[PDB]
Each structure stands twice: as structure tokens, then as C-alpha cells.
Image (cartoon, helix red, strand yellow):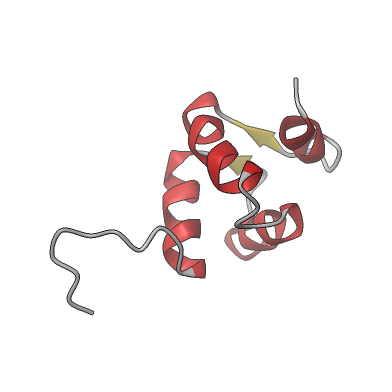
Length: 72
């Protein structure tokens, strides 16, 4: 489909549209690299990047810092 989609499949990694629609924006802009995405899933020991992973990822790396409260 695309570079991002092909990049994952290259390492036997799959991605859902729910996460692609979001991860694409953070990937296309040049925020995170493919190497970082795979490094995250590695710690989780999984070959499926779903919305749950995408959320924890950006939250782990420290990106998209936009919260209504923002405490700590």
C-alpha cells in the first residue's frame, strides 16, 4: 500500500487501519522512525500494531503532549 505499510510487512509486522490512520500522521511528519516503532513492539513481544499499541507508543516516547488536564 505505502512505504510505512510496506516497511512493517518487510519484518513480518502487520498494522491495522485504525492505527495506520494515526501512526501515518506521526510517521509522515517525521516524528518517529520505523526503527523506533519496531523497537516498541519488541518489548511487548508482539507482531501486531493496533490502536492500543499506537497510543502507548506515543505516550511512552513522549509525543503528542496534548491533555486537557496534564498533571504528571
